[PDB]
Image 1 (cartoon, protein in one colour):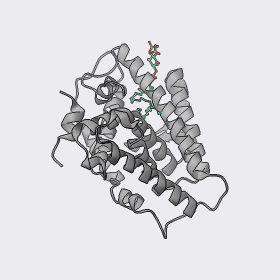
Image 2: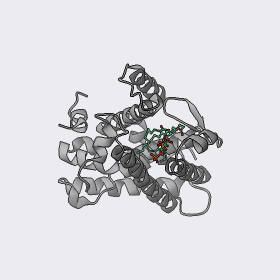
Image 3: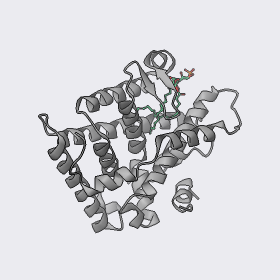
Image 4: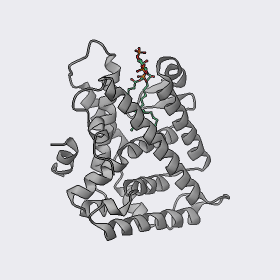
Length: 244
Length: 12
Ligand SMILES: CCCCCCCCCCCCCCCC(=O)OC[C@@H](COP(=O)(O)O[C@@H]1[C@H](O)[C@H](O)[C@@H](OP(=O)(O)O)[C@H](OP(=O)(O)O)[C@H]1O)OC(=O)CCCCCCCCCCCCCCC
């Protein structure tokens, strides 16, 4: 539903969520900048790479303002982000599709629509499968009636979805995870009138998001091995980070 | 060294 009794963490997360129009304008302006266009590639490719990069910039900016995360040192933050970057980006795309859903197309962060036929005829089988599976996930989330509260809560959960042994500040992160799960469970139990464990189902959705993220990493890696990615690409730097 | 570290150390 809406919210008479929403967990404090979820409310604070709602207040920590950036404005869509501002981010859109910022990324657009960041794309408007001149660039050394490669003659052996469609410029749209580089523009989309830069787009994803800027999206991740905004995501990082969102992370920096988050509770618990801002109480962490640089190392832990870098580890977490290097662990959940693709997941955060993918989930961002997915929820962007959920919030503004036209089944015949996908909506980019810039605001431009891309029909599924275009993807089906112009993209490779891998990216096609990625978009299709992501759209299936979008359909599932729409079926579960996902709201903004559960969205930001799930983002926060994703941000700290990592084994504790790779982090220096153990107890704090543990508290963050437990509090996050407790918040999600509380909200879902207090607001979902339908049947089924919405909490567990959302966790499954998170698993699917993770696998999808793995596939995305695989795609970016394929582009990387073919020297198709622009130099100093942020996502490639995140991909080349030491895995935890 | 890394753009990520620069981002995390950037002014807020
Ligand atoms: C961590 C992931 C974060 C992603 C979040 C943002 C998601 C943005 C989605 C972007 C959708 C834009 C699609 C616009 C329409 C479109 O389909 O245009 C084409 C597609 C790409 O065509 P192609 O290169 O695949 O397909 C190639 C192409 O045909 C070559 O010409 C062939 O070479 P060839 O001529 O020698 O055969 C290749 O063959 P090969 O296999 O050998 O390399 C083939 O695979 O649009 C693109 O340019 C997108 C550029 C990527 C920038 C952003 C990174 C996205 C990475 C993750 C995917 C996001 C999907 C979401 C699902 C979770």
